[PDB]
Image (cartoon, rainbow, N blue to C red; front, side, top):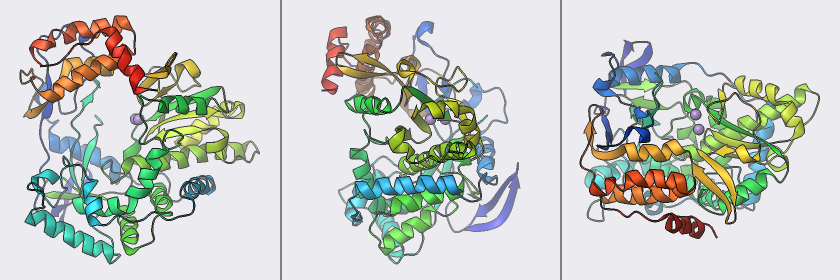
Length: 493
Ligand SMILES: [Mn+2]
Ligand SMILES: [Mn+2]
């Protein structure tokens, strides 16, 4: 499905042949709640500013093309080294011990399809969402044709087309031109990968509180306590990192190793063989009538992105320390055990041993030399160690209460839910909306109270003062401070 080469702004692309075009969705679902006082505003804006961005050139196709260029750059690492190889042995030993040596069964078709959520686009080959083809309990003709072919091919062990549908992620971003792309996965790759990786990932999700892979953790529960106790079980210094341009710069050799590691304890069938071969191949994406090939990166819509990304992080964080130990003449090993750490995509929190604190400059540089761009989680200061009462993970800070440990979403994330609302219609600019009397907004604004309560009565009151004004716009309840506080407590215990 590549025809004749395109050359526009510096991307290597081709005219889409053999498939229908997949035009990206313009505009944004987000719109402004009317009458919001200025003290509640935080400065965030939709990623697709539209005609609210003065530069006329900043059109969707240009923006997407600009952000795709990055993925066509040659990767930092061409091959994995000895420290990443050491770290891979750790992950392998963690999984082999988790699974008790037993291989995880493939799901059959029905079970795998059932794991896909109804509201997901079907990828570049089938229009609409999953649910637009599975109405009266059964699949329609188009989806079934496509899914039977993919399933047949995959069970013969041959790889599938690792193709996605391109677009701009519709989300709120600060006032600063990098912007996240949408990698809408082909439904056939999705079902096949779900058949192969769901059982091992279900097992990982149960054991998420212990980590290192945090995918599945519940930041509102006792999970938080086991996360924190574990961090302080071996150290009294910590590191909180986030990474810029993570997805877009990931090296194939690392991604490929992550996939091999995750499939190691899977049932060794032809379907697994096919899924491994598919996800390991350089992913392509269809912008409109153009198909674009990549040279680096991990598509954030790859089936099981979070876990696979989390293995990459484990590999790279553990190698960076191991490399830094080697330079000082030390052999370091078993990092995840000796210095417990957690990982959720590009987000991580690590225990720092005295030796590791001393090796901090060399570790950040070793992270740089693997192609990553580390930054402090506390998005204000430089990278340094941060104490117990300062740790940050998954946009949440922590506080030791009588009901164990308690997590607080950063105040801005709460506040922006008062300023913005994810409407069901596309807006071509920043503007206000009155279509706010929806059940989904209601459950969001009641939940927002439980979120705010964690910051104290004064913040709760500040938020509720605006929430009480929005009760004319949305059918919902405003709890008392005590009532909300009882909900946090109930969610733990
Ligand atoms: Mn980041
Ligand atoms: Mn992050």
